[PDB]
Image (tube, rainbow, N blue to C red):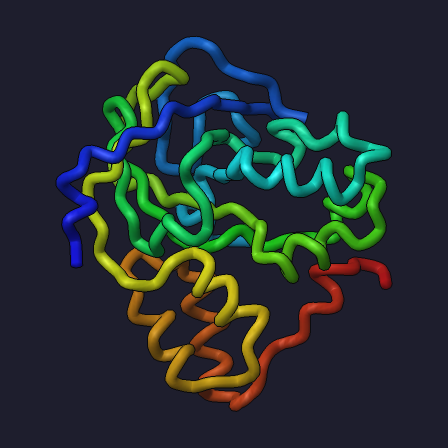
Length: 218
């Protein structure tokens, strides 16, 4: 039921951009493709304009790899948005947030990639993120506008009943289930690339391979 829409959920947010990303302190324009100054000019660009990573996960990583605990600080995972209070289990697919003059929508769970394995110098960090579901999520930009580190993320519409955690699990943890794929394809706001993957699974009757993405040349 959608009574969360009326609780005025507000989440203070730290903003990072780059071409390691650097913290932005003032206001900046959020365009269709991303934050002005953030790695700008593989289709589906509009669906991955912004990357979010919960600071809660750094606690977990620092405790899993104490020897390199200094590395586990925002924005080590490449995120643009850093917060507390928002995780894969309470963020739903299609969630629409008002952010200053902008409108953003959750489009998919973030997909761990092997580049991460060389960035943290942890050979299997991409596998680890995917296995724990600690991946964060991306946003599509519904309405471009000025945003800032000062304006909080405000949840305004909840329009699906599939959380990021569920989408992540449906994609990478459970065995082939057509019904589950039909369910994920029904979630509002789904990125075109996730629609494609899930639709390809229904027609092929198989789960595509994850080896190259997670391990690159290995």
